[PDB]
Figure 1: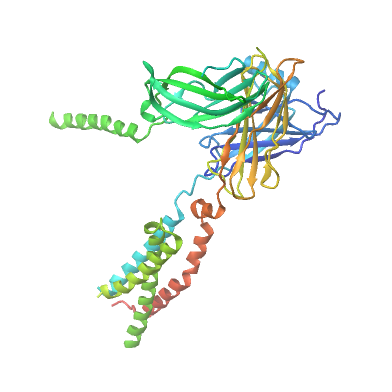
Figure 2: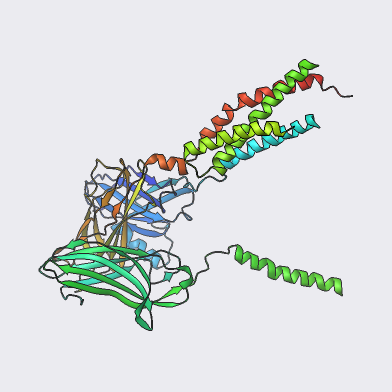
Length: 150
Length: 153
Length: 61
Length: 162
């Protein structure tokens, strides 16, 4: 039974430490509430065209979908996760298979995952930065010292 | 040790059947206990063997000792991962995957889940310096040649 | 004349010496003793930086 | 038998396991059976709340249907609150092999025994000490900057050009 006026309270997680994590994992969890009290409603999640079946937790109304990606592709920016019910999800496969526009089908709701980028180690190590600034300071003093002693 | 008729196994290669050299390969073994008695999964093994002589081991990969129990009419999945040497690419190898399991009574059964010759593939993922450096020379050789021709004539 | 020479020699000697100690410590601690146990790195960096400056002070004449 | 066949893998997406940081657990389900599985349930009780802290993700979930020759994924984030060896045991998955058929119980892969490191080893190895360096430069400003000006101010008074 199609959810009427679905109210959602989305929460998302994203990998921010590449040194420990082999990949960048995104997790979108939705505790969906329906006006018709429709429990156990099948849901699907579409990410940039890739279809992921939304997971249903044991607690009523909680939903989760998690899709992983490689570090070299998990570029910083914004991610928009779209969802479609079983009725609409059937149309989406037809549109994709028939190469019709995927935007023509409106999604039940959208969740945006704001990825700020993962840490790939310092661009220039602070120690190297520390050494140069001090080394530059030494040379200037060395430039000063020689001037006096010359 | 022959494969007991009460046990059914499967192997699924996560990233397809391509075995790229110097890259992690992952596959998942499945075990089904159709018998009436318990089955204990001892350890899973993999090795490389000569295509023309399966009796000659080339590389033996560390065994994964599972020592896990699969009761009757229950399924179990086991992950095994290994990294093939970089130079092996572009040459075939006889890849063997064996599952070792025993019944409570002390009988040992072995199942060669995957017994086929597999090819390690060549890769060009990026234009690293070696690609550029051979780009500088060929252009540079012509640049000296083209410039050299102008001066001489 | 002595007061200016006395003072300015004190400051520039003071200023030059402090820079060399810190700069030497940083490089030695994080580039030469990068693989040493912090006390062992601490012992060597501080000693080498201070000890070398002690020897370099006489090595500047 | 052309019933459903689900191969499950419970694997860790962390190169190391370090206390207090985020630990990744990925459950991957592959439907190598010819018929689509129905009412797939996965339960992971192997993690007590005392040791691992759930940051995001539900250990226990259910899926309505899985098509044949297809796969599904599921990830959960945990934080090891302590340091010490842990045996990452197997999970349990129940699904129906055939429409109105017997429930098939299956076990997911087991990572095995994995060691968890101590935090103080990591911060000294991969945590950037931005703020420490900035304070260090200010900490060394009084030792260097003031004497240089004190010298320079004297130079400003006697360095009269000829």
